[PDB]
Image (cartoon, one colour):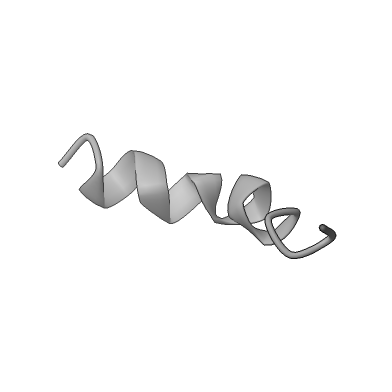
Length: 20
């Protein structure tokens, strides 16, 4: 629900470690 809605905002750090 509105939970995953938290990932987008985290998409920042994600871009950091994911593409680290």
